[PDB]
Each structure stands twice: as structure tokens, then as C-alpha cells.
Amino acid sequence: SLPIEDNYIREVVSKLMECVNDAVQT
Amino acid sequence: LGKVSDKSREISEKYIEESQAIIQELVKLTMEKLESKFTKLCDLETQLEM
Image (cartoon, rainbow over the protein chains, first blue to last red):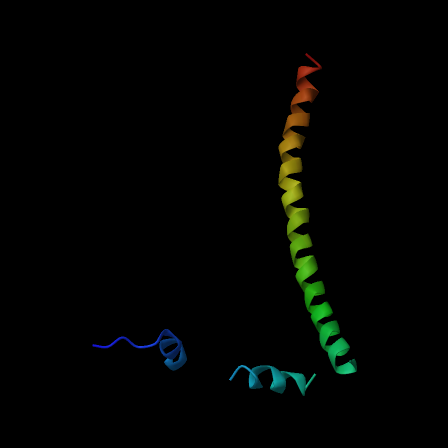
């Protein structure tokens, strides 16, 4: 139940191909 | 760009077919509203002659 340091608690804590395949044809 | 311009031009032609299909409705709808004023105008043939 000893308290822990605060600077230790703060220390522990498909859409591509749909358009590419359309860009190669036209 | 030629592949995109030619893609847009058939889309431009697609909106041309979209255009006149509305315009051929507007000529009809103008007529019935005009026909609402023919029968209004034909009343004045008799009322003024009275």
C-alpha cells in the first residue's frame, strides 16, 4: 500500500485498389 | 488526359441526353397552363360582345 511516483504512473501509461484500378483504364 | 477527356465527353454526351428529356417535359407542361388561359381568353369573346 505504499504510494507510487507520479512520474512513474505517467511513464507506464481495400479503398486503395478501388481507385487505382479505375485510374489505369482512363 | 486524353483518356480522361474522352471519358468526360461521353459523360458530356450523357448529360445531353439528360438535358432534352427534361426539356421535352417542359414544352408539354407549358401547354396545359397555356390551355388554362385559352379558355380564359375564349370567355372574353362573349363577355365583351355582351
